[PDB]
Image (cartoon, rainbow, N blue to C red; front, side, top):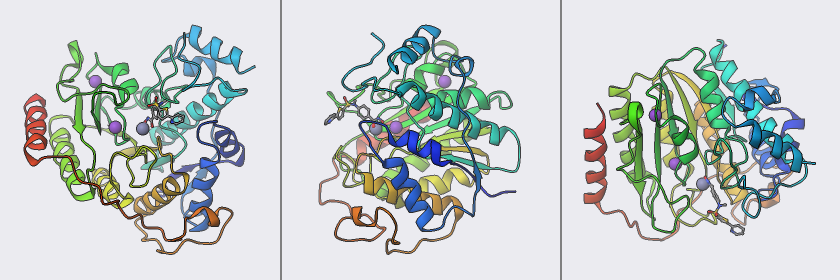
Length: 352
Ligand SMILES: CN(c1ccc(C(=O)NO)cc1)S(=O)(=O)c1ccc(-c2ccccn2)s1
Ligand SMILES: [K+]
Ligand SMILES: [K+]
Ligand SMILES: [Zn+2]
């Protein structure tokens, strides 16, 4: 077994480290997890590289081939620069989430972790927001070999548009996303009015949130909507993305969460006791993202972690404080009690 599965292999971590816009985060994340000796308490499973056929269960051959070519418009460039070996990078992530999926389809595993996955923005034929391959989607598509109702819960700061669009017309998968929704804020979509299309209408729930949201309030919103969604929908399996770009101190500077808030949310989903695929995502303050995910790793394990940071390779990276906890800034919570209730009521009606 009941020990969660931890997708890892030095080759995978190093391949993940080569991501241009987020260098070394994989190692840092794994290193801190290892430092608290959190691993060796999970079932370590090596990642399998995704094949062309597998990745194409969503992406088009046109896009896959092209990507494989430059690794030697499709959304490539500035935000998504096709650096050397990027195709390999993508295939390893995708492969990694698909193997976490298989780990769940089979037994002896109620939770499968791939902190390096979670790129929800990738379209079937286009890279977007640092996302080259949509692993979350590939995991969901794998999970559906055995589960008729999958619940996708996206807690990244950004809207999970890629995964949502992928299933907007089906009621097999239900995508729920809590994100910042403001005029010029990427990807600029996902208002509460967004509920899906055709046969998928009401199977896409979006929770537009504003800057400054803190642990408490965030959790009340989350539990409120999740509880409602667990009722109407009878999820057999669950895919959860935990982008840490919501954590106080992120360069993104929008939400004001700490891993503990996001923690209560995790605990809430873990208590349904369903097959759960854990993914990472955003998180541009490399040190905090590591603190966030190793802590959440502890929450998956239940074992409370030592407040002081354990000596390891990146010990220095832990600011001046050197503690596991993260303190929110003194920024205001631009979320009025009335609009949040209004949003909740809208979706609450929608759910049928
Ligand atoms: C590419 N972009 C994304 C998209 C998605 C994410 C994300 O975390 N999604 O969950 C992050 C950045 S973006 O256009 O909004 C950017 C944000 C910050 C960017 C940046 C890039 C270089 C230097 C400084 N800032 S680009
Ligand atoms: K989100
Ligand atoms: K859907
Ligand atoms: Zn994000």
